[PDB]
Amino acid sequence: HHHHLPNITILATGGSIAGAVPQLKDIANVKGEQVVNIGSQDMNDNVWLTLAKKINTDCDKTDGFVITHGSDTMEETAYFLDLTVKCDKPVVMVGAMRPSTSMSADGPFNLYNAVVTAADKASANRGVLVVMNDTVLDGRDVTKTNTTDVATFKSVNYGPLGYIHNGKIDYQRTPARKHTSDTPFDVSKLNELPKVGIVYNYANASDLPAKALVDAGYDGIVSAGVGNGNLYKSVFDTLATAAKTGTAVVRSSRVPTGATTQDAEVDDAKYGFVASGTLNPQKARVLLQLALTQTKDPQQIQQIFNQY
Amino acid sequence: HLPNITILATGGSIAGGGDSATKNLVNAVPQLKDIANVKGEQVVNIGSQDMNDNVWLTLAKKINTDCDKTDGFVITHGSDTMEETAYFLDLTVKCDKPVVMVGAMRPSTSMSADGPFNLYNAVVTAADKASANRGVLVVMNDTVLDGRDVTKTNTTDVATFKSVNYGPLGYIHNGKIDYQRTPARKHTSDTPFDVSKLNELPKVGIVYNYANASDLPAKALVDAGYDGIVSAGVGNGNLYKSVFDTLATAAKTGTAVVRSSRVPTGATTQDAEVDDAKYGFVASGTLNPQKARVLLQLALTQTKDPQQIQQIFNQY
Amino acid sequence: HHHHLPNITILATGGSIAGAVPQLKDIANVKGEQVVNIGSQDMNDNVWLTLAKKINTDCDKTDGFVITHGSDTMEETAYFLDLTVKCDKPVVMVGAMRPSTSMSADGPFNLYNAVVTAADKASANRGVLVVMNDTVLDGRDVTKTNTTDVATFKSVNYGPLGYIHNGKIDYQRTPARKHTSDTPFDVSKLNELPKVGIVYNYANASDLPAKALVDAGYDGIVSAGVGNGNLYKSVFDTLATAAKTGTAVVRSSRVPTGATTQDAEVDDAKYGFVASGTLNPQKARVLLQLALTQTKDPQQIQQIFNQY
Amino acid sequence: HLPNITILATGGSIAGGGDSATKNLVNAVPQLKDIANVKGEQVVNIGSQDMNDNVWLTLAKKINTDCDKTDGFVITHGSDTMEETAYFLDLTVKCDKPVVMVGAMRPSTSMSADGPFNLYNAVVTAADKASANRGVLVVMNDTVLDGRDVTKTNTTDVATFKSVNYGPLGYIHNGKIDYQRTPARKHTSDTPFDVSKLNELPKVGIVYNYANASDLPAKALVDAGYDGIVSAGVGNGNLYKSVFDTLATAAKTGTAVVRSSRVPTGATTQDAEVDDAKYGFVASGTLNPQKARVLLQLALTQTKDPQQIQQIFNQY
């Protein structure tokens, strides 16, 4: 029985991350589309919606997706797609911490291993994935850990799903949080997403950013609080008042690992707030936006934040 | 002959016990009697999530005024913003005697409360002659950490405090420190920041970057006339287009603008994907956003010139 | 319906780690047995066999086990029990990096959370566990990372299974490697375990340790090699010769994280060696001993090392 | 005017390419021409899993002999044992010019090979005036690491090399280094170890601890008359009873015995669960077993007295 290489679609959102990688046509039949071409620091709602509708639409036509993405916001898009993709085939985002034209450019081998991952039958049903520096990382926990390191992407709370050696993956973990077709989030018909902004906390923090998003009518605000999701008093006060009038308010934390818990120093039930768990501010944003498509009920949003 | 150690408290008790009435931290931790002569003062009482410029100015004046009246300082402080105060004092304290900050990640009435042993080791540190001229320090989880790099890495772990870029100065075992490192960046009496005469600090605020980021936080700070704005950028200090547009205007209209990053480690570098000179921005290096705010505030007490601010950010 | 606290047995192998913790009788009905009393640096085969036979024997009589253990070798016993326990109820090992009589002693809260973990219905079917510093860690990957830190125990390759806040656990992972009742390893009738020793590699490494265990007739030798399971030439040569005459030889690595892979710089098939994967030397020992109770066939031992 | 950098190769090529015949590392990495004047020498050709005392003695003599003939040194070396050679040279090199070691975790013919950029940054380091008097260095993955603390933390990761106890000295961005740290432990010309006249080194071997550990490795080293034995202990240097019994006899019968630990970070401390003075042991501190072996070997060229060995282990 002859060998039959799987069909992998590469959806590009930005420039090239290798530049191509000839060794790919030994492990797969690759076709490419350019969906957008933006620096990922300009990543946005409309790109997310395109990617989710594109993956869900083209599911039938291929064996897996690799998405090439700037590293800056890959962790946000990864998680959005983790929640909105309904396609049962592997979806593997990949990027490069050194540019394709650089010495020891890292994109070529990351792309190789991204395709390996996307062709591996064992990668399906693990959620949307991020493959970087020989590692398969779940889209929920993966975050950018260092501003330059090639090893920067890590799942800082629950670890990676497997490591990649010589084109093979040893999977020892899968995320237990509900993803992809187990979520109720369906963007197939949405033209926009609810407006969710992020305010930082720190000593002497001004409440003017919070007030501005409130006055703008934002659907939700994520607080990147201090410690275990705590807020500077003025920020607290502004966000407490907004919640009494329907603004969703998720307490996250600027602290780079660890859950922002319930039943700690903030009485969320009293105040109408939601605890983000291990979702960092930009990740809590992704889930809050998608939550607000179902409900503005803070008890139900908290539930969503305990399931997804 | 034991060193005199002053304890400046800014909140609740880091350690409990020993308070039973015959008819207070040196009772909670009786073994302080073995290593120092401890006197305490309550400077303020607040949770550190409410920390503010006024407390900072108080602490630095208190230490610089009372330097000659003691051999070292321990500051008990909430853990949420400890890393911001430690860097502030690291730049404003002119006393070369050790200033050690400590807190607790478990409340003082809880099983396996960490405050009691933390306070002990912080006094050990404050009392070690070798701790002098290392800058302001944070002592947590058996570890001496420099006030510049130290940061809270985890929301609940007792080991949360780490110097995530250049690592600790020394470890504490059995009341002794093996220092193998000292911060090269200029601190305490090698900085020009003098806050002895200041009743306030320049308004500096922080905005976050993420996909689809609103410019409304940045614009709100511009409308209030903030003297500086720290961007918590994505990756190496990069900016969402709308935030970029607003800060680019701000830098040319009197606002000092510093690119840091939301990424928890690594420098936001010059000569990367933002032409800082074109835009009048300053890059924060390894200073995360809250730490960058500290140096930008004090930078603005000396200058508004973005090139002088960048040299400051390359030195302190 | 009144509350009914679960019955947790604490098997002690050494001194006290708290000293007791009254808050335990709010979350469980605790009974204690002393199985042995040794410093865990003298941990041994006979203690392991006792613990496995005791857990399997007393399964019916309780709702979960907590085992208090010295921290030095907890990661070895944890993994042994991970492979030999057949009891479907939680088995949670716990220890203390500061002694019970010390300031801010860590044992009392570790023991609390060990019991929480052992009483949590969600902890069952996750393998044998290690609970340390608010964290639930799987017995296979957990290792001692620092010589003194209270946070020392971490699953350095695949991360922890959940974190413990306010007596509750958020499980987001479970180990995929086969454990407990999914292994064929049955020590219920064994009086001894096959002899497996560990040799270190380094520059100018003497082959005399390897030779001594060979000459002693050791059933298996684990090499704590350098890098990706490589060996100093003289150690290599001695171990190659022993394998030709039936000695099992597993290539592990002194390097503290990362798999010792197959298909790298050693041709294991040629030489009769087995790659340890992410099992560090002392962990590879545990699995090799148990492997040699089934087989001396290096291809089958390699398979075991890819399944357990 | 560019610094002269000598490259001592101990194995294969760290970088390939540029070798096409008109009818070699400065061709593989043409951009060396921009930062230094590179001359190469092949000292030995071996995989570093086979590294040995003879290579060590060669490298230290070569650097100390040719110090005056160049401005700095880069040593390309296999990654398996790099951390052992870097510490050896850190104690035996008397040239204060930078000695930078580099290797590669991906082979030089592989996708995204790391050697080419590693060699570049190692030359950057060797060529930076600020890299002098910091001891022998390892430059991997954009990071200057001190030869004492640096270690291989992961079997395959390109970022494997870390100073797991006290952290890096500086990071490399765009051919520049921001040094914020320097090792306090005494190195290079501040040590008494002089190997200029030595054709061999004292026999020092390593034994592992684990449950049910055989004493046969330890006894085998005792039977061969080894001058030292490093224990890779469990936890804080603790010993399995049978290994303990054998090393306790060994320490009183002429064998130097050093307690290190298999645990990948933290010190094996004095004044813990082993009475070192009772037994004539020495504690290795933060030196893992292979690094402890290095200093014990060189310690034994000066003394067999366990108390003098412990002071050495407290100083270097």
Image: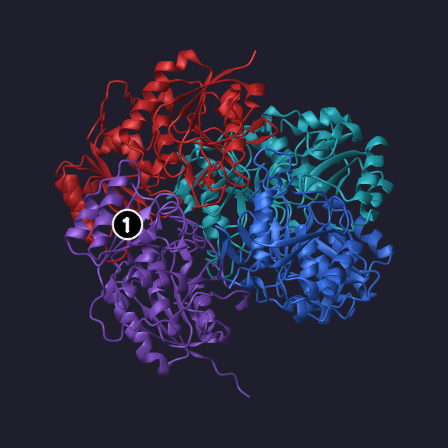
Chain colours: A purple, B red, C blue, D cyan
Look at the picture and state if A47 lies above or below B203: below
- Taking the view exactly as shown, the residue that stands out farthest to the bottom is A1
- Res C261 → quadrant: bottom right
Q: Residues within 10 Å of mark 1 (few under 14, many from 20)?
A: many
Left or right, A38 with reference to C205: left
- Res D236 → quadrant: top right
Q: Residue at x 75, y 53 (%)?
A: C198
* SS category of the residue bearing label 1: loop
Say whether residue A67 is visible: yes
Taking depth in this image into account, of C216 and A246 the one nearest to the observer is: A246
The residue to which callout 1 is attached is: B238
Left or right, C161 with reference to B67: right
Locate residue A82, reporting x and y percent: 37, 67
Q: Chain of mark 1?
A: B
For the C terminus of chain D, the quadrant is: top right
Look at the picture and state if A112 lies above or below A204: below
Look at the picture and state if C293 lies above or below B24: below
For the N terminus of chain D, the quadrant is: top left
Amino acid type of the residue tagged 1 in the rendering: Asn
Say whether residue A35 is visible: no
Left or right, D224 with reference to A254: right
Taking depth in this image into account, of A83 and C211 the one nearest to the observer is: A83
Locate residue C25, reporting x and y percent: 59, 50
Q: Residue at x 79, y 52 (%)?
A: C210
Locate residue B207, reporting x and y percent: 25, 45
Locate residue B298, reporting x and y percent: 27, 28
